[PDB]
Amino acid sequence: SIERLGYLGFAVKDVPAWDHFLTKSVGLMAAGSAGDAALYRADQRAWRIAVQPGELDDLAYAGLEVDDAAALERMADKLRQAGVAFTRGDEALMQQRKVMGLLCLQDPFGLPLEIYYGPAEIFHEPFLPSAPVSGFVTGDQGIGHFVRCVPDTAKAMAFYTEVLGFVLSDIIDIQMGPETSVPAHFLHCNGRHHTIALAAFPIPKRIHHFMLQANTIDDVGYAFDRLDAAGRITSLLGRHTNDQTLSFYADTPSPMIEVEFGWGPRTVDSSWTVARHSRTAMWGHKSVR
Amino acid sequence: SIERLGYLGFAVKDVPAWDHFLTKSVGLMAAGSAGDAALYRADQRAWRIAVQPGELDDLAYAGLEVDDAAALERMADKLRQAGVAFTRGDEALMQQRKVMGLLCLQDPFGLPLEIYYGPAEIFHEPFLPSAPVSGFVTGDQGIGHFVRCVPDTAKAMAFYTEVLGFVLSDIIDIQMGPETSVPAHFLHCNGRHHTIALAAFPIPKRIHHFMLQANTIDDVGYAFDRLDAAGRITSLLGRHTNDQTLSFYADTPSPMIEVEFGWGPRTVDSSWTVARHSRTAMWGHKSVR
Amino acid sequence: SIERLGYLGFAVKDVPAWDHFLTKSVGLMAAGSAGDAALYRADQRAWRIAVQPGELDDLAYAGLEVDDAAALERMADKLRQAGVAFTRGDEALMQQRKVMGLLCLQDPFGLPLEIYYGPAEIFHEPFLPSAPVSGFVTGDQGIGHFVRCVPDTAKAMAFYTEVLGFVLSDIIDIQMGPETSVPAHFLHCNGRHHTIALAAFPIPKRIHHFMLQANTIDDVGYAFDRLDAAGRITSLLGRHTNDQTLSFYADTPSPMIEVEFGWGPRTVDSSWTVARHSRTAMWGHKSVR
Amino acid sequence: SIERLGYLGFAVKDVPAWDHFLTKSVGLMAAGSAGDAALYRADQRAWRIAVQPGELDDLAYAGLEVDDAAALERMADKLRQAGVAFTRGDEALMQQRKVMGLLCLQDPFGLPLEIYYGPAEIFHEPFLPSAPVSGFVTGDQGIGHFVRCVPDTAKAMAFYTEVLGFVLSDIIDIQMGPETSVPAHFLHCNGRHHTIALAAFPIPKRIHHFMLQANTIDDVGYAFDRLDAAGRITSLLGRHTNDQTLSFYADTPSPMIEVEFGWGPRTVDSSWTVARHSRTAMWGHKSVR
Amino acid sequence: SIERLGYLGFAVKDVPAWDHFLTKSVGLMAAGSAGDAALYRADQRAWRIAVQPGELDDLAYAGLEVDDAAALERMADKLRQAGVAFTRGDEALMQQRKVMGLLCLQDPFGLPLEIYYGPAEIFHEPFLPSAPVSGFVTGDQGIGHFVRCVPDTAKAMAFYTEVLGFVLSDIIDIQMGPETSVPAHFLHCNGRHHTIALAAFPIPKRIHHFMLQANTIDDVGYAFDRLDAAGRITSLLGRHTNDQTLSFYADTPSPMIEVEFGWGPRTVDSSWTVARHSRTAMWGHKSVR
Amino acid sequence: SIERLGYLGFAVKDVPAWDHFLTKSVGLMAAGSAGDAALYRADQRAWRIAVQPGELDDLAYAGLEVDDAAALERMADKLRQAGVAFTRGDEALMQQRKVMGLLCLQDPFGLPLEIYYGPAEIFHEPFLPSAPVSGFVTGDQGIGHFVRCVPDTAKAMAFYTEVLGFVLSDIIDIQMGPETSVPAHFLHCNGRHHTIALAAFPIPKRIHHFMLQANTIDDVGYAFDRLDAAGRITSLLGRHTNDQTLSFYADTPSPMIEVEFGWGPRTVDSSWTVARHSRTAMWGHKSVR
Amino acid sequence: SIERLGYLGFAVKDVPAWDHFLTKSVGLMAAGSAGDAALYRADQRAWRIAVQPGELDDLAYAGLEVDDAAALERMADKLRQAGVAFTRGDEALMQQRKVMGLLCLQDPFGLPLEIYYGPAEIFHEPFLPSAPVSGFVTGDQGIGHFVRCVPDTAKAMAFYTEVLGFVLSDIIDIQMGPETSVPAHFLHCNGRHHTIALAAFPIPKRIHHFMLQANTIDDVGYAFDRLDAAGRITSLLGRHTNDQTLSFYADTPSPMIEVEFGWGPRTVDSSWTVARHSRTAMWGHKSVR
Ligand SMILES: [Fe+3]
Ligand SMILES: [Fe+3]
Ligand SMILES: [Fe+3]
Ligand SMILES: [Fe+3]
Ligand SMILES: [Fe+3]
Ligand SMILES: [Fe+3]
Ligand SMILES: [Fe+3]
């Protein structure tokens, strides 16, 4: 029922650092501010990523998008039935997020979520990258995806699939040590292979990384050099086994939070078949961190 | 449930003026008369626009099309259930409109509507424009669209969506003054971004303008010169934020009633997402009136 | 529910004449016999048209095809419920028609119909025309169409649509005299604009004509010369207003029964809209008979 | 060396008749006048066909187009070398024809020809047909073609090919009587199968007919009805053996001068092979005159 | 300079056998006769293959086609210069071959050749196969190809390439025995990989086989069954190493003369590179004879 | 022989103004400096436009590009033969222009030209617009075009065509007053309709305007708003008669020097035909200056 | 005049190492031997790369391919005229290289070259990679390219371009140190951006590296892992500035000789323009050696 991941908000110790990072390195377009949040664009939306000051140095909230007012009410009904606590956003928050309506809640482990509809668009102010990137693949598939760290994967799954409507794409057993592996669960809610992945990682953050998809392979290759020059590279170029995203990872200014910049993944449809993978990389992705 | 806007009828103080306007300027094909109404064609339909003498100088009625006899009966049932008053058209009116069946009613604010099915087509008399226009985009998306002025938008919405079946595409807050803006609601009932838009405008007419879509950009550019020569231009070429219709506006011979001539808008489908815009123009559309 | 018109059987006074006609003029492939019926092919089916001796000089029966055994049983249930009398074909008839199952019945006015499934195909004996025709458009749309003459159109309609599942495409008012016109009703049951049309014609036959669709326009042009040389032409080339079939008509050896040979008609889909036409010809089709 | 047939001028006894004919029947756009010549357009050229008063009731002259000033001078040199008499057009004639330069001459049998370059175009006045025709195929292939009647075909050939540069496409032996046939020679100077054809016909005119090519088959079918209603049809629809032009012929208001309206012919290229045909019609083209 | 192989003439001991073979097995269309030669068509040409009575039971002559009259004269000049004896065909022979002009000669080893231009075409009598074959690939690439047996390959090469203009495509060393192999030389004169191949085979005939190319793979598969039923198969289906023709061979009624029926070979262009192959078959082509 | 217009250099009274103009308004990418010239990029070239301080406020020089070293030498030979004075650029100038070789000269009326080869490209520094423009159409067609003002058009023509190799596309008679018109000559040297146009305009500058071609129509529409906001618009959107460039004009910071921003013009090829036009605008282009 | 690089032969100290390398790492297909040379295939050619024992540990010879026998003779004539010493290969060498003819020579600095024609192909033994690679891009563009180290670039250029016919694509100044850069010259002889590049590198080998082009990007990514596992990687993935080859470099078992494995480069045509680049990498290609 959730249609796609619409936006992301971070609370960070170094806002200027994040600002230079999202613009000069990632290529996002600086789009003013809202309250104490610096806004960044990747397309026609008024904003896609917000950065506000905070000791968390983590993802502060994620906006899950539905297609209309009725859709939002149906979601409220679903939350009620599932016994999930939520608060309807007030005029102030609606004004802040630039949405027509939203329900604020949390997943089983504390990550604030905001189900909303009616996002603001500013076509009269065409997107202009701050670095050389031909553009980002968003649209119906949203802004990108992120891997959510959870203490209990089965519990996170029930909520994301049963309450929010995400559908399992596949699983990848991620080798942690000699005989230690974590089964990462990749979920989709539209054509993007996965919008949210759940994994029991020994990480002190709400997420491992967030991913943005560029239009061309050169976008990625160019982006890799920009981040290598910034000395932020954590992995060499590679392609994933399940979604086939060709990408590289890099450190954001927030310790233990990374960004993935990729291109050309496979998409999901009705006939999608659940499968299991033993490795995350088809090829490449050698760790550099 | 209404499938598309099929026809439009105007009651005007200057019929010869409207006649020269629809033909020499807009390019429509004169198609004889019915009663005291001059008929005009834009394609294979026996008529699409009718012009009759009247002090109103406004839209007299709008024909909403359904795909068959059963569809019309289902609509009657819906009107009954909604408590909406209607009268089945008699042989005379059917003969006049050249339709197989129709229900006559009014929207909440007095605009006569006629739900019909089985329109007449005259393929043996191929459309021939009266001015240089390659053709119009009609077909499944109907004749075009119009913006309906209403005193109460919420009330108009309930009727058009709940009773007639239109679906909200998006909203554009139209700046009226210093701190005055009107939220225009754009509704679709097929692939055309919108067939009817509702807005609380301080206009003494039932509508602000009606829109026709030509096949090429040159059609529009050529049309702009024809209307500029007639001195009717009210806006320069531009493209809208929501549907991306590239067009210009011009005054019809009826004061405060305009026509929009455009090309290449985006179309709507199942996956359409409701959004909000702060401006009507992506670019251009500078007021000239 | 009927999926398409699968076959046609004629009972004629001059079988050799019909044989030379279907082969040398129309181009069908002679395919042996079954009982006292000469069989003719137009594609991979064991037969599409059968010709047997008889004083009728008219269509003897029409095979309406469904996609499987269950489909046929569902149709029997429907006939039962509608009070329509029918007999399940015996081994003998199944053997004769080369089908896996069939129900024999009659429409409201005596035309024998046979609802069947599991037709026989002989791919090991590729279709070979008897005259120069690149091929026929059949497949999912069946063998072609025919216009059924009826005394009561409303009564025929109820049966064909309500009992058999055909859907109205459109209507054409056919001028008969000074102030006499017959509203022909065109029905579809798949992508072919119409498989059966009903009209109250003052003709002493069950049908006016049957139609076959060739692959190219040259097929038709070539066919016209072949039939003109046989002196059978009844109409010049033309294109119809509703389906846009480009064709010509010719007399079969059975008096008052004609054949239509055409190309490139428009096809029907979910979004089809019922409409009315005042003429049968878009252009051409001048009577020659 | 001649690049294409650019224009045609007729001298006729009934100008109003020719005017109604070229516009209401053929669909050409009336384009004012030059001297005592009424001009008609088929596309972006200022004019393509001119009609002036005269007892001839025949083609008065044909404009053969080259691509530039040098090209015209090279042609003058060629005429000089071939001993062909010519006169360079004066300012007056250049003004009249709306060309940048032209050489006036005659073919071996008296038909005035004008080799020119730099034709005038009026894109600011888009072509608008006077009858329903989607458009004409001109461009690099010129306005169309015409069949030139000559007393000596071998003599006409030497001139058109050796002096003017036309290249033989093929020949069609046209049966005249019991044992009388005329070998028509079809010549091209660009992609159009033929721009000029030569034949020893017992006709008292400089040409048999001129041909115009419409964009669609419906254009032709529609045109046939328009001319049949005018009672001018001389041949039924058909397709030619050599160029495969699908067309019909009709009488112009000038006795023994016809017009051919067609669609979809084959085009010529480098690899074209000369061939011989025994008939003019692939199919159709039955004489009606 | 020769443009393509246009026709073939055989002199055979059993004409009725060859007639049933070319029609019922190969699928060619019987096209009457000329003198004592039975003619057969494969497309729009008046004839492509001729069969006349004779003790030879071999290829009697091959028609090499040029694009026009000048081309033929240029070829005569070339023959003169090369000292090759030739005779211009008289009206009688021109009438017999249905060509506009031809030069009769012989290759270095006695095979009569006829260089001609202006072949006759009969589009008013569309090709109609005598057996199920969708059509043949001819056109600019001619009727097909044949392998010419010669006592001296170097001598044959000089003539075919130096005098007639054929260009070497490649060579295939054909294993004859333990340590005996014949280098077959494949020559092209257009896009067809080869129109004539030369090889020093111990065969008492002028040729080994002639080849015809069908439009689809099913054409070939179907043809194989037809000839297997006739018990004429000499090789199983296979694909050649150099041209990639997928085909099978079969015996004609003339002992030691075979026919090849194939599909989908590669074509030749300007950039073609000469190469050498050790086998004739890429796969398949197992001998059955 | 000149292959395309590679670069442009301006000498202006207000460099900061030109800098803000080329970047914020036009969208070019600032690319450092060379000597006292500020460089700007539109694609992969190290620079395309240079701006240096000077009282001229006009085009200082134009770089005409050839494909290699030999090409440049052939051009020197041509200049020698034509008696045109030129100087080979020294290491310093080569270093300044970033080219491998260049010849410096002047056209008949003082505009410095530099024929060069081997331009520098910096793919490792991807083009990044300074304003929202999807990109520019350059490549084989160079950077764009410019209209050169000359006192004697015939004299300018001889030089540009006879010495430099440009080819005339067409002419447009530009109405100056009541009975005063200037015949503008448009020249091409590649697929771009024209790279240089010559016209006898009463302007005190070397050029009237220079033109840049964007990838999309939205690029232009967006650009128009940016320049209108800067209050520099001199013409409304429109499309030209000859090249069909859809564009608008605007004033550069240099008085009487304008810029044209357009999209979608037609391109030129071998078969191009010289023609004459009476107006510059197909539609639109209303003067605003 | 040389058409493409056909083959390469190496003389190496460790043949088994090279064998495992070309097969298990690169993916080439082992194809037996010739004399003391192990042969390897990448496509339909009998062999593309040969490896023989030798102390050189360098490229032993390069086969330059022409399209036919005449072409080879024309090349001999050219060598004679240029005073370049050469020896026609004997039966033995022809047998060894599997070519129909070849001329053996050396470039100005000792690298043996063999101009040949008529290479052997074995389609009956389809290419089968020894490692996972979808295939290689060869065909008309040959096997790949190599960078030739030379002491005098101007001298090497004159020979390769003036004697052998290669054409300069572009130049890249390769930074060697603080103020030391080597101008690498890239030459083409077909569509491949470059087949041979010349550069004054301080390397004790005849070449720096040879390049092979795979069909997909995954081929390269997969290949990179295979060679990284072998610990041979010398550069990370990257894309070149001039040809845009996306690739990585790796060490062959021969010290100071590398291999480049890439995909998707740009191709060259008639309109190619010579240009200069300051870096070899568009992005990536970070040194790892
Ligand atoms: Fe990821
Ligand atoms: Fe509108
Ligand atoms: Fe019909
Ligand atoms: Fe004609
Ligand atoms: Fe063969
Ligand atoms: Fe311009
Ligand atoms: Fe390389």
Image (cartoon, coloured by chain):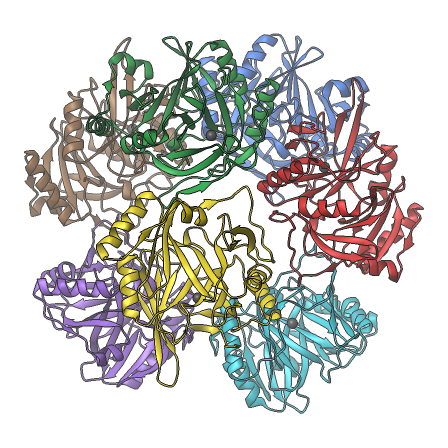
Chain colours: A blue, B red, C cyan, D yellow, E purple, F green, G brown
Instruction: Answer left or right for G217 relative to A194.
Output: left
Q: Is residue B61 above or below residue A159?
A: below
Instruction: Answer left or right for C217 relative to G94.
Output: right
Count of labels shown? 0
Q: Quadrant of residue E83?
A: bottom left
Q: Is residue E261 above or below residue B248?
A: below
Q: Quadrant of the C terminus of chain G?
A: top left
Q: Is residue C45 visible?
A: yes
- Expressed as whole percent of the image width and height from the top left, the position of residue A102 reads 77, 25
Q: Is residue G284 visible?
A: no
Instruction: Answer left or right for E47 relative to C224.
Output: left
Q: Nearer the viewer, residue C114 or D80?
A: D80
Q: Is residue D204 above or below residue E169?
A: below
Q: Quadrant of residue F36?
A: top left
Instruction: Answer left or right for B43 relative to G132.
Output: right
Q: Nearer the viewer, residue C76 or C263?
A: C263
- Expressed as whole percent of the image width and height from the top left, the position of residue G24 reads 32, 35
Q: Is residue F175 above or below residue E211?
A: above
- Expressed as whole percent of the image width and height from the top left, the position of residue G171 reads 28, 24
- Expressed as whole percent of the image width and height from the top left, the position of residue E213 reads 34, 65
Ligand 7 placement by image quarter:
top left
Q: Quadrant of the N terminus of chain G?
A: top left
At a point 79% along the width and 28% down the height, the residue shown is: B183
At a point 77% along the width and 47% down the height, the residue shown is: B16
